[PDB]
Structures are given as structure tokens and as C-alpha cells.
Image 1 (cartoon, protein in one colour):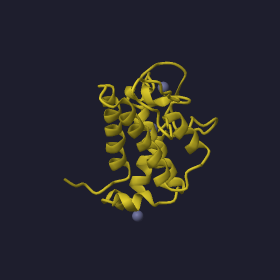
Image 2: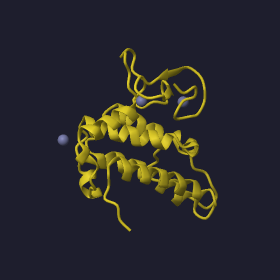
Image 3: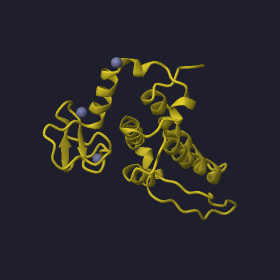
Image 4: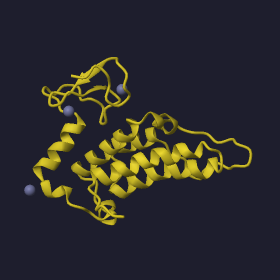
Length: 178
Ligand SMILES: [Zn+2]
Ligand SMILES: [Zn+2]
Ligand SMILES: [Zn+2]
């Protein structure tokens, strides 16, 4: 197995996947690495299994249809993985914890949002549809863009949103377009 966490790229107290060579810190994995379970399969393996069991799940889909799906176990898992994929980018540190807003010439957002809050919301099964999760994720970046205005720091929002969106299209097999 790997000697660093797949998500944060640091060594430490790591749990090793039994079906692939990835390793994770306990709370870097999403969901948090389970207490017992031998063997244990990580979320990358669990997502691969879903695909292999239903090859047709990779045919293209309309985003509108994906968003209206109820958060049954497989959609819950796919959102957990998509959230993990954003945490895998080091620039996610900017959006992880609860932000605050005091900048001359700007006003804070009406509805602040951050990755740790989405993580808790998923853990507590607060989303009933994929739409709920996707709206919160997109809100994180939209709030950032609106607040930082013409400061070049706005680009961090664009960058992390692109990681989100690419992984969203991949995981939920959105129909490719120009
Ligand atoms: Zn880690
Ligand atoms: Zn694995
Ligand atoms: Zn089938």
C-alpha cells in the first residue's frame, strides 16, 4: 500500500485499502474509515464496483435527471466520493472551514457555505436529492466569486469549481458535449 494519505498527501496514522493500494487518514476518507470491517474497501473501490455491476451506468446522462435523483445509497456514495475528490486538491483548504467576511467594498454572502458543512450534512443524511448537495457545492464557489470581485483571489474559486465540475461530470456520467 501507499505510505501517504490519498487525499492530503501526508504520512501519519493511515488505514490501508484491502482491494487497491490507497491509504487514508481516518477523517480524510469519506465516510470516515469504518471501525472494524476486514477486509475494508475504500470509496474508490466501492465506486468501481458500482460501475462494474452496471456497465450501462456509464452511458451519458442529462444533468437535470441526475439532480432529481433521490439520495439512495448509491447516490449518497457518489456524492461522498465527489466531495472527496474536491478535498484531494490542496486548494480546497480555502473552502474547508467556515469563512468570514470583512473586506472594504464588499458585503458577505446571504448564505455562507463551506466543505466541512457539506461533509456534516452528508454524514447526517440531510440531503434528499442529489440537487441539494450539488447546489451547496456550487454555492461555495459562487459566494467566493461574488465577494472577492476583482481581486485576483477570485481565481481560487474558479479553480476549485473546475475540479468539482469535472469530477461531477465523470462520477455521474454526464453526456459529453461541446
Ligand atoms: Zn489525509
Ligand atoms: Zn481501494
Ligand atoms: Zn446490469
